């Protein structure tokens, strides 16, 4: 059914429907599908779904010139721990990714692989099954006492990364980035947000290290910036974006309650702009908004009111993607896209609206999303959300 209380506004007349160059790609409009974990990949081997994923992505690529960022994709076994999320380290994984990318390119849209590493958000017992470590910035902090218990129950306690461990993650990012590009992706997005491994190094709650990877703003930023630099130099800066969530509390991050958190992110962005000034500008920065501090909460819940991402615009001068409860607030988008380098990521309503871009252009009602099929091994709730016309052919 359609979202009941929703009054659509047509955005055809705004910068949301003006083209923009992002890296090597040429977008027709600035409505971006952000990374969305859907757990349709098959076990063993974290293989993308061969029946439905190319259909799902192709449906949502239908408007030519759409930028699509894939679900989080593991760079290596050690970086994972979720059996039904995809990887891109292996030949069999890349075999299906080529077909997904072909489905998006057949629609004249673009595909960016979000490269993922889980750190303390992983499952210690699944990792142990596979002979893998339970990795974190500092083993003196756990997400919660439950994951602490399961960690001890699996005899796989948190492992503070060594310097050699970090170097191996950097190699795995390079490997996964190279596989992404050889498979046909137009670029990659380094996931450094939402409390996963790289965010765990940025945040002073998770990162209590005393080597060169913690203890200061500069040290906490080092792992993320080394991944950035490694990929700049192997696939080029125009094929690399970075995702950050300054105000997020998901996965036990500090958010705005830490008064030092804007300095931490301001340092990362300043370092990105320095690289751009020396001729190596990343394709984009992708920010999660304080509008959504936790994506497991319904729209309007978990909204942080005492901070904004405006600081980013004074530091980073390249494209910025913003994401968080924009689908139901066209009045906010209308304002924010007056800035000529701003794109809007639409998460949960891209799940439910394959023709979301058309609906935003024409101001049409939106399909409700069904939270119970966000993560089921099913085409139901994946590829069977109707387009607007189909929805009217159904009574909605
Ligand atoms: C089911 C679901 C899966 C998501 N998966 C990812 C992911 O793999 N990587 C990521 O960076 N963000 C992920 N997110 C966060 C979204 O990209 C987005 O930032 C957030 O949902 C807020 O945007 P929205 O209100 O438009 O949905 C996910 C969110 C949801 C709801
Ligand atoms: O499954 C939800 C999810 C949220 C944020 C992410 O970064 C990844 C997955
Ligand atoms: Na390879």
Image: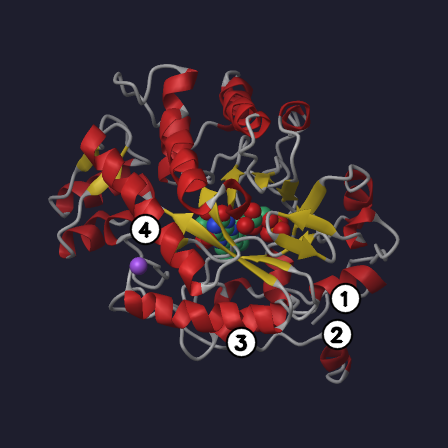
**Label 1, label 3: how far apart the Cα atoms are:** 18 Å
Return the residue at label 4.
175
Mark 3 or mark 2, which is nearer the start of the sequence? 3
Q: Would you say 210 lies left or right of 294 here?
A: left
Which of the marked residues, 2 or 4, is nearer the chain's N terminus?
Answer: 4
Question: Which of the two labelled residues, at mark 4 and mark 3, occupies the earlier sequence position?
Answer: 3
Indicate the quadrant containing the N terminus: top left, top right, bottom left or bottom right: bottom right
Query: Who comes first in sequence, dot 1 or dot 2?
Result: 1
Give the SS element for disc 3.
helix
Task: Name the residue at 81% across, 65% down.
Answer: 364
Label 2 or label 4, whichever lies nearer to me, is 4
Foreground: disc 4 or disc 3: 4
Q: Indicate the secondary structure of the residue bearing disc 4.
A: helix
Provide residue 222's location: percent of width, then percent of height.
37, 25
Whether label 4 touches label 3, CB < 8 Å: no
The answer to whether mark 2 and mark 3 are in CB contact below 8 A is no
Quarter of the figure with the C terminus: bottom right
**Marking on residue 388:** 2
The verdict on label 4 being within 8 Å of ligand 3 is yes
User: As drawn, is 296 to the left or to the right of 159?
Assistant: right
> Which residue carries the number 1 mark?
358
Q: In 3D space, how far apart are the residues under numbered discs 4 and 1 (Cα atoms)?
A: 37 Å
């Amino acid at each position: 059914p359609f979202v009941k209380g929703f009054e659509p506004i047509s955005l055809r007349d705004t910068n949301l429907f003006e083209p923009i160059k992002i890296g090597n790609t040429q977008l027709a409009h600035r409505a971006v599908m952000p990374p969305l974990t859907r757990m349709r990949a098959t076990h063993p081997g974290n293989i993308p779904n061969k029946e439905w994923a190319a259909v799902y992505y192709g449906q949502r690529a239908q408007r030519p010139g759409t930028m699509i960022i894939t679900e989080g994709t593991f760079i290596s076994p050690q970086a994972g721990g979720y059996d039904n999320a995809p990887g891109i380290w292996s030949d069999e994984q890349v075999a299906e990714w080529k077909n997904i990318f072909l489905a998006i390119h057949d629609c004249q849209s673009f595909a960016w692989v979000q490269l993922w590493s889980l750190g303390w958000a992983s499952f210690p017992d699944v990792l142990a099954r596979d002979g893998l470590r339970y990795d974190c910035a500092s083993d003196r902090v756990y997400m919660n006492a439950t994951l602490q218990e399961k960690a001890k129950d699996a005899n796989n306690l948190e492992h503070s990364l060594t310097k050699d461990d970090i170097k191996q993650y950097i190699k795995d990012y390079i490997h996964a980035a190279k596989n992404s590009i050889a498979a046909g992706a137009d670029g990659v997005e380094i996931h450094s947000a939402n409390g996963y491994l790289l965010n765990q190094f940025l945040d002073p709650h998770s990162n209590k290290r005393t080597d060169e990877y913690g203890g200061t703003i500069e040290n906490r930023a080092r792992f993320t910036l080394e991944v950035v630099d490694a990929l700049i130099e192997t696939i080029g800066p125009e094929r690399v974006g970075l995702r950050l969530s300054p105000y997020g509390t998901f996965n036990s991050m500090s958010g705005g309650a830490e008064p030092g958190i804007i300095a931490q992110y301001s340092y990362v962005l300043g370092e990105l702009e320095k690289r751009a000034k020396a001729g190596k500008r990343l394709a984009f920065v992708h920010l999660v908004e304080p509008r959504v501090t936790d994506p497991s909460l319904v729209e309007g819940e978990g909204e942080y009111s005492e901070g904004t991402n405006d600081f980013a615009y004074s530091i980073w001068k390249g494209p910025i993607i913003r994401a968080g409860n924009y689908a139901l607030h066209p009045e906010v988008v209308r304002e924010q896209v007056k800035d000529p380098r701003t794109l809007i990521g639409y998460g949960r309503f891209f799940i439910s609206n394959p023709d979301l871009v058309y609906r935003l252009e024409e101001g049409l009602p939106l399909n409700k999303y069904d939270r119970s099929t966000f993560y089921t091994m099913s085409a139901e709730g994946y590829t069977d959300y109707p387009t607007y016309e189909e929805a009217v052919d159904l009574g909605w």
